Image (tube, rainbow, N blue to C red; front, side, top):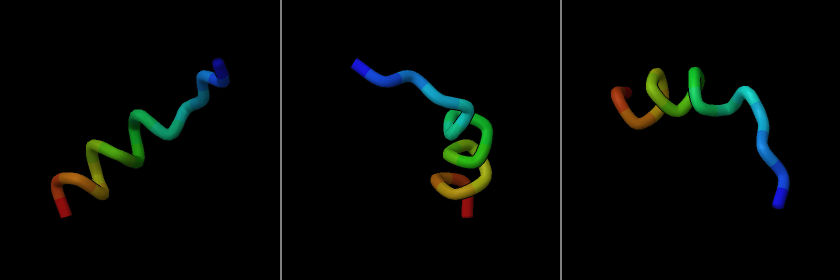
Length: 16
């Protein structure tokens, strides 16, 4: 219950 723009960084983090 708290959406954010961390999906973009996750693509960069998870991809890291």
